[PDB]
Image 1 (cartoon, rainbow, N blue to C red):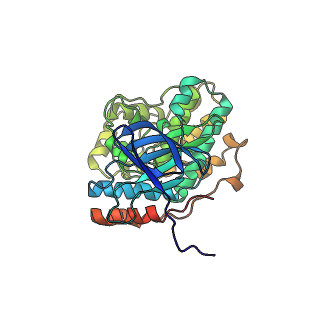
Image 2: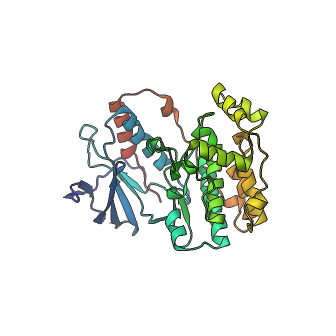
Image 3: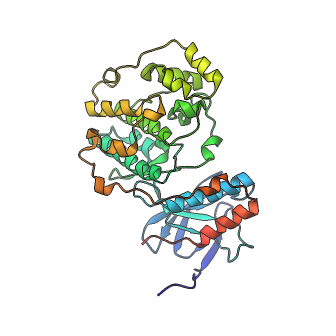
Length: 355
């Protein structure tokens, strides 16, 4: 009645685009799909679930302490998430039969074709389509935030949408966003809260609410809310909308130079959001206000947003689950490469697939 043995499937070996792919035979007809510095990816047919899946062979997962710790951190997150608005892990394997021969990590996920950009390129979304997506984003973030994970890079390129307008969040909780350049007229930095983009204070899950506020506004108007040609420009665009900070917010900011800078800016009142988003549903404008609050301590939570009147057609407290606890002790801990490799191997071998 209890399992003793992990029975090991049969793997087959092949070369596609000068990339060795050794995988279980359950994965057939692999198609090269692309190669970034985050792994090579193949489309594949999973004969056990009937789904079509993305197989991802990590690239150089253990080449430095930083990168070893990134491989583990990502694998830990993917394993933990079990919510239909969050990319789950459906399988993770390696050809290695022991930690000594262990080198490669493959990650199996739902093949998720289109992202929120591609969706907006092809249609003008109806009002109900927009509402439904903000709901799902907030629903998956409620989950994420329940387990004390901060997405840290929530933006349209990190949301996958299917034909029935069903949404999953991608790429949450990782250190990789620091590898993109955030200088100039760049989309990555356009969705970030001012406090992390100028490192006024340290991260906070409220940082992600700022992001969904920026996406919602883009989904209602079709325009980027804050397309700043640089940090300072983006900050000015922000303060114009939400108003210069007050005393309670300025003392929360640790750098003495940054408060001198803010108080050098000409003080401005907050703008009237009804005159900024002409034509929008008043309930949508009301909720935007509560997401776009300069002081993160006063931003709305995802759990509060779901209960806001804008979502009355979709809100149901009995279908908005929270996650199990996510132990992140390991983030403060100082290990060697080989030790991070061993903990990654241990989670690879201990993976339990979904029922």
